[PDB]
Figure: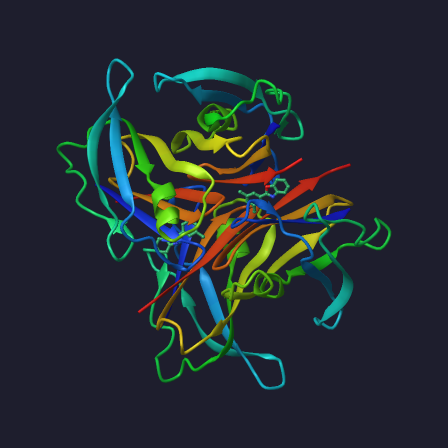
Length: 114
Length: 114
Length: 115
Length: 115
Ligand SMILES: Cc1cc(C)cc(-c2nc3ccccc3o2)c1
Ligand SMILES: Cc1cc(C)cc(-c2nc3ccccc3o2)c1
């Protein structure tokens, strides 16, 4: 139900081997680790969770943009990109969190489908 | 070798049934029709051309954003979105022209891969 | 030294009355409240801090996009937009944090100048 | 009534010395040259036209992004960014055409105000 896709606006390519961490907000308002991985050669990270586990709640997707740029020998602005949203059962069932990265800028969009 | 993908930033969905026209720049500097179609339920338009036909040159991808918004009952700013680029044989072989649409704004990125 | 500007991609206008909260990473790694305000009729928020107070650190600029959208009758996707960055680590700079908002998408850019 | 502002997403700065050509659709459906200029050190281009001259029409703002990038040693993807819109068809408005540039990506937003 959750996929993350990352693109590099400088090179016009997927952003490969980017670390991504997902957290779920706990009842005490802290962020608890939920799932993680590294984007593939296609810039995608699949397999993070299951329908059973991805219950309604507030989630945060943290994308390690700084390490990505540093590996390319480029100084970037942000520490990371963070995407924070509520998962809602009464909306479509599949969430794609997309991010488009530049050194001093990023875009993120949610594509929510059935 | 050429795919076009269009997303709707207002609804968080693919932009479906969007008309797309591709032109190739002729020797006399006019734009000649090259290929066209409508985006699918996934917001994608595949099958526009072939490797044989997609020779080096300057191409323009025109996305009929205004009709898309009007069909949703929303007044938009732009007449269309236009993406103009040179196809280069010494780069990767597959070009994805992506567009992210809002009523008063759009983003476009090229993802060029092997 | 720190300004925030927010635009609305739906209406083609400044995003007015957007709440913004700034935090700074403390020595204990918690996010300490640093400054807050709301965007004006121009979509800008000025006067958050001073060059004396805006020391080196890791800052988080939280833009309350959900609270903004709900008021135009849009149930938007994100809770807020968070912009996290190291500031002033090569000496004082001026930072503009710009954000462009749509209900299911946003972008943010930093413009950094050396006075 | 017509301003263009351009930012560079790579450097986190205004995009300076960017050429901009504006055209207007003529009665014969050709693109007639309307105004041109270059962005300043602030990334802004002011003074393109006057409210008298900026009549209703379909306008195209061509931003010469390739010419810009080639100079920072980036071979970029696009030839230019084209922004095409109907203006002033409900009476005079003020238009800001903003663009955010990366070598393989750009975004553009319009801010439209009624004086
Ligand atoms: C935030 C943003 C900006 C742009 C120009 C494109 C996209 C985008 N999001 C995508 C999700 C799936 C496949 C292709 C996609 O392209 C996302
Ligand atoms: C992150 C972003 C993306 C785009 C296409 C535009 C802006 C933007 N933010 C602006 C604030 C004041 C004047 C012009 C502005 O343009 C900010």
